[PDB]
Amino acid sequence: HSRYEHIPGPPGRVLQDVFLDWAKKYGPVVRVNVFHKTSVIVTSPESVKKFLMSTKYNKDSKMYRALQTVFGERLFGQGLVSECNYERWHKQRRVIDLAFSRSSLVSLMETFNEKAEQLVEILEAKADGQTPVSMQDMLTYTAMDILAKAAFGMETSMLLGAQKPLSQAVKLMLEGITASRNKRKQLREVRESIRFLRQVGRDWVQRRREALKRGEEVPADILTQILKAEEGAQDDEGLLDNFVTFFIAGHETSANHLAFTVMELSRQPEIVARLQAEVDEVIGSKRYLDFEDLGRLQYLSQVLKESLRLYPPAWGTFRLLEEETLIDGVRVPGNTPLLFSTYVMGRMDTYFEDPLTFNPDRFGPGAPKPRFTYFPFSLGHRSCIGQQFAQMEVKVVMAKLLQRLEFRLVPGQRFGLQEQATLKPLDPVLCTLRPR
Ligand code: HEM
Ligand SMILES: O=C(C1CCN(c2cncnc2-c2ccc(F)cc2)CC1)N1CC(F)C1
Image (tube, rainbow, N blue to C red; front, side):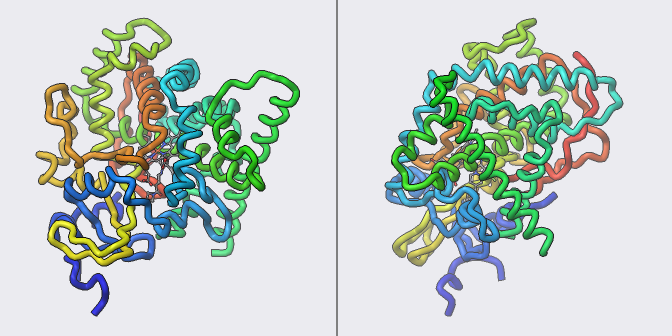
């Protein structure tokens, strides 16, 4: 008699689609196997509210092992995403929060604008209606160049075709996370890629420390606060865990969200005409979007919320259930990982009418707000520290694309998903482009 046997469950697609099928068939508490562990997927809004909105429930560290270390190489270690002890998390969260204040983020608008403008100019030169362009690749290069400058004061210049070894290292590390949760050459390429990313942190931290000593210019950035959180530490391993955490987390989900949005909008010509009209009316001929302009792009804000409902790059989270608890009529044993999924809840007709329809008007003013059914940045104390940074950067990039260019998805390109650390388009989002 297995400890989970009594829980309801089974006797371009991802595992999350299988979980969706099972939540619909077996109800709000279902036993699954994920990251090699038995867990329970909990899909009632009452459960999302109870477990995400209380500091009583902490993240289940077992479900973060493949971010902490891959194939025996330390990756994110005990950085801000993967630290599951409340007190150790809270200390670093409150120091790093200062880099995400309103004043800190408004000062990044110049960087967001400059990299968005550079992308647009590169794309405008290819806008012949014939040359295929990977929007997944171009949006990833743009997100990387933004993050490296905004967070670290470094110029990666991926939009100029630079840092190819770094681009390969990130790709192989993301494949390593995926393989670890589900040979000789794979192990070697993944392990060397993780060590490369930590050595980039060593190199960049040494550059920052030399700049501070020589009395050169250093703007207050995320790296300032990562350093501050480690003041008086025994070694640099905590520093490098947060360096790699922010270097990867600060670009990959943003790129995924951009690529999903461009992909979906390629089959939504009326919505695109509305977004083009909105950018035309709000920013006009301006080459630079001001902070005050972002809040005026209200239809774009709704489109991006709807993109996250259907295509959340980070599908959810886990909490550790410490004691046996009744969850929606089901007895869940103590020491169980509870899986929460914004991907699954977003596709359930219980929670969203016509869930596969892309309808920005779900997020219109005076529309009833989703109540614990929608959480692409999670909820509660472990919600995304980067949520407003991401929302600002992606609005800037999308507004500049919409101002200047028309995109058509190359026929044959698919709308399917893949999972490698995060959810992202299976295909490269190959488009042809024309100037507006
Ligand atoms: C559209 C883009 C993004 C999405 C969808 C997203 C999503 C999420 C989600 C779902 C979580 C909770 C993860 C968990 O419970 O294990 C999270 C946490 C986090 N994200 Fe993001 N994120 C985005 C952008 C960013 C950016 C831009 C940064 C950094 C600049 C970032 C850094 C982090 C960190 C460090 C955490 C851990 C926060 C904590 O536990 O205190 N994210 N994000
Ligand atoms: O692994 C994950 C998530 C992966 C996405 N995370 C991010 C959050 N915000 C920005 N970026 C990321 C990022 C991107 C690339 C990456 F390799 C790791 C992290 C949050 C954690 N778990 C949640 C549990 F179910 C296990």
